[PDB]
Amino acid sequence: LGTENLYFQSQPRRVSFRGEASETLQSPGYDPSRPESFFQQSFQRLSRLGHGSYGEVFKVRSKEDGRLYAVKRSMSPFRGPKDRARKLAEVGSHEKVGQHPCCVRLEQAWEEGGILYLQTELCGPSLQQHCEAWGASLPEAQVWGYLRDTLLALAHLHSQGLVHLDVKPANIFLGPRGRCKLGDFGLLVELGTAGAGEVQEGDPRYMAPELLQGSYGTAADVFSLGLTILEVACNMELPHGGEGWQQLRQGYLPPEFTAGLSSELRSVLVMMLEPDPKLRATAEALLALPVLRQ
Ligand SMILES: COc1cc2c(Nc3cc(Cl)c(OC)c(Cl)c3)c(C#N)cnc2cc1OCCCN1CCN(C)CC1
Image (cartoon, rainbow, N blue to C red; front, side, top):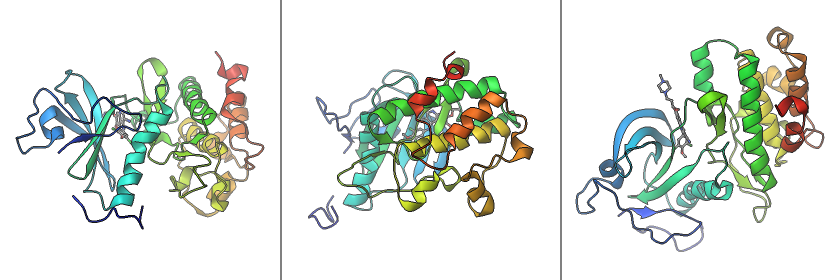
């Protein structure tokens, strides 16, 4: 796209790779001849759930159906066609993941004024926030449930040759009754992407060791989930680098933090944290273990 005639050109339009009956947006509360954006006119903005260089995520109430949702709004208008294509790919990735009970559902998406909006179901707190609120290691009964549900999500992605690439507590969202959903598909890739790459990098704390050499595969997510579960089960801050980062990628489980794990949970984490991706367990293989079935 960067050598194509796509530069220095140019109101809401639906974003959907699947295909739609219409790219026009309508809503109770929305009049396209008023100057406010579709987002401003069509939602009650209740609170800001998150913010960063990417933009902002809001908790909102839809005027179309009176229900609660999350809406992510990008920070500033598209830089150009490559930035636009990268950001719209997130919608495509949702549509490639589709509907699955352990994956956050995308309700709709649109662009207006160079800004991209993604509207998802509203979940409970992120696993990161839940652990902050708990203020301690999570009880293992909770951990097993979150591990199972996130593995079910990964098995769904991986069977279709998709790699999430940023599995971490901030991208897992609690539901009722001890369940959770994997979200945030902004870094997701379809392997053999025609060809291989380009790729953006996930949080270094959770990154699989083989990614340092550019070896991208579904195994990477199993490793990242392994460290996610180690962190929440042990209330253990993960290093971004240095000796400790290396050690966690050489089979080390720090005794001061991990001695209180059940033997069963420790065993499963060792399988997930295997440094060699060719030896690391798959999500399907982990879900077949009896400890993960009940
Ligand atoms: C950070 O909080 C939440 C983020 C959520 C979230 N992220 C997200 C990511 C991305 Cl990449 C998106 O773009 C596709 C979009 Cl649109 C949303 C999705 C999703 N997906 C769904 N549901 C969420 C719910 C949240 O918090 C609910 C509890 C709030 N409560 C906790 C107690 N505290 C004192 C007050 C705040």
